[PDB]
Amino acid sequence: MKSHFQYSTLENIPKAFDILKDPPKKLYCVGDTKLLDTPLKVAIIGTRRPTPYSKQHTITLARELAKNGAVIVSGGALGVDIIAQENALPKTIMLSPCSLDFIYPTNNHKVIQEIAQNGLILSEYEKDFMPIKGSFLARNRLVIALSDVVIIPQADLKSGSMSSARLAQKYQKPLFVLPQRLNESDGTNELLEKGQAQGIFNIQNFINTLLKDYHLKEM
Amino acid sequence: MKSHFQYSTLENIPKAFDILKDPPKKLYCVGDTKLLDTPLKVAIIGTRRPTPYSKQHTITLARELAKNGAVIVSGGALGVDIIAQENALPKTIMLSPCSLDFIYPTNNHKVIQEIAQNGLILSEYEKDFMPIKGSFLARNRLVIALSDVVIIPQADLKSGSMSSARLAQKYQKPLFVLPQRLNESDGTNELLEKGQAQGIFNIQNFINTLLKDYHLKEM
């Protein structure tokens, strides 16, 4: 699916990317590059098939953070990603796994269009580049490096979410996850089990504690 | 409801009760007092109103622990208690909130009778005593003191399970809970978030680690 987006090259690579083993040498952009200057960026990533439970709290977290000064960063994927980003509009930044002349995934086209208009989409791929395993992985590192904090509402083991969670640890980004029952989100529960992530046991307090840590007003 | 239990004096008060600020001065018993001389006693306590999820794993915990050399200790209450005890039979000990000439609660009479017959019931009251305010708290102190480890599968804030949880901490009895969703078991979740309990993220590993720790053959 062609995007028909009008895009250009990003003038300056965010310094947040310098922590990366292999920073992007060149980035392409469509939308509001001012979003890159915001004080609080929160990554929200997760499974392509969240439960109603996960979906419900993903919406609240995204909506409330975006409404109170944060910018939500994600990969625009089916499920948790696109849910967070739609509910954060227009304070949201997407890292694309393909070049900006294409929409992926197809079914998210409507929301992705709205991000291109009112939010920001970045890509490391100039044109004609359909997504492949390595480009999903590569853009995940950008999602993590760009963000101050990383939330994973729900995720299985051996998922992109878990490789991103490893990156979050490697790059010292605080990891947060939703409390989940046995067997429903083994990835996030493993992170809890090993003390590699903090549980979000109260949505409003978590949000307010984040706002304060970054000198924004609470709710 | 009368029990028709031919209860005895429990002649030797278990040393485990000696840690209490107010040890029971006299105890009464019916059933197998040898259960008191076992290497591993696990308290399983919780809400009177468990979800199907909590119920399902309580059954598994109780059954597997009882089958592999542990004894399950509880209060015989509606919900988690009676579920755990029924599935632990005959390796189970009930601490009764009433004298042993009565059944309490009435609706648990069948399992409670099975416990009198094949497990063990203890009480701090001799006769003619139905429970009153505080007698539940009182027998809970006994459940905790007797047990090596305490499992709370599900519980609300301000419940009896939480006051028992405070006792477990006071006496350094390790405390474990089931992973629970936001807004379902605020009691156990608060324990988890405050680092006061450990989560059971893998039922089989939890059990095998517990066993090993008490020099029992792993499953």
Image (cartoon, coloured by chain):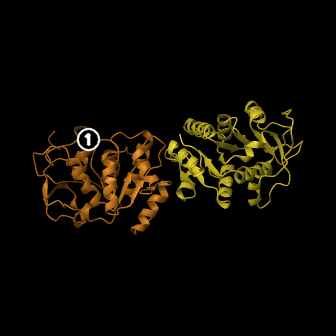
Chain colours: A yellow, B orange
Residue A119 x %, y %: 74, 37
Q: Secondary structure at mark 1?
A: helix
Q: A45 or B14, which is in the foreground? A: A45
Task: Examine the rendering and report whether any part of residue B219 can be seen.
Answer: no
Report whether A159 appears left or right of B182.
Answer: right
Q: Where residue A158 sits in the image (x, y, percent)? A: 66, 52
- Residue positioned most to the bottom: B215
Give the number of callouts: 1
Q: Quadrant of the N terminus of chain B?
A: top left
Please state the horizontal and vertical placement of residue A191, each as a whole percent of the image: 57, 55
Residue beneath the point at 11% across and 52% down: B126
Q: Is residue B165 visible?
A: yes
The subunit letter for the residue under badge 1 reads B
Residue B22 is left or right of residue A159, and the answer is: left
Badge 1, how many Cα within 10 Å: few under 14, some, many 20+? Answer: some
Check the image and report above or below for B18 versus A143.
below
User: What residue do we see at 17% from left, 43% from top?
Assistant: B132
The residue that mark 1 highlights is B108
Seen as rendered, the residue at the extreme top is A110
In the image, A40 versus A110, the foreground residue is A40
Determine whether, in the image, residue A37 is placed left or right of residue B175: right
Residue A81: image x %, image y %? 68, 41
Describe residue A196's horizontal placement relative to residue B136 as left or right. right
Closer to the camera in the image, B86 or A74 = A74
Report the amino acid beneath label 1. Answer: Asn
